[PDB]
Amino acid sequence: TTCCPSIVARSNFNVCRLPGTSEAICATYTGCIIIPGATCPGDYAN
């Protein structure tokens, strides 16, 4: 599951994914995170 810190970061993440970039690279690129669960925390609400 991916969780993002802000709207901007999520929008950025989704563009990063368009060419097929791994989620892990898009995460460090944007400040989004990958978690094994499905429940994003309050400070990664977007």
Image (cartoon, rainbow, N blue to C red):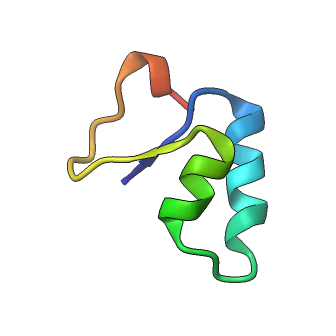
Residue 9 vertical position relative to residue 11 in the rendered view, above or below = above
* Relative to 5, 39 lies left or right: left
Residue 24 vertical position relative to residue 36 in the rendered view, above or below = below
Task: Give the position of the N terminus as an image quadrant.
Answer: bottom left
User: Residue 20's x, y, as percent?
Assistant: 65, 82
User: Residue 12's x, y, as percent?
Assistant: 77, 50
User: Residue 31's x, y, as percent?
Assistant: 60, 38
| Residue positioned most to the top | 42
- Residue at (55, 42) in percent of width and height: 32
- Residue at (67, 70) in percent of width and height: 17
Residue 19 vertical position relative to residue 38 in the rendered view, above or below = below
Q: How many marks?
A: 0
- Residue at (57, 62) in percent of width and height: 25
- Residue at (22, 53) in percent of width and height: 36
Task: Give the position of the C terminus as an image quadrant.
Answer: top right
User: Residue 2's x, y, as percent?
Assistant: 44, 50
Question: Looking at the rendering, which quadrant does residue 33 occupy?
Answer: top left
Question: Looking at the rendering, which quadrant does residue 7 occupy?
Answer: top right
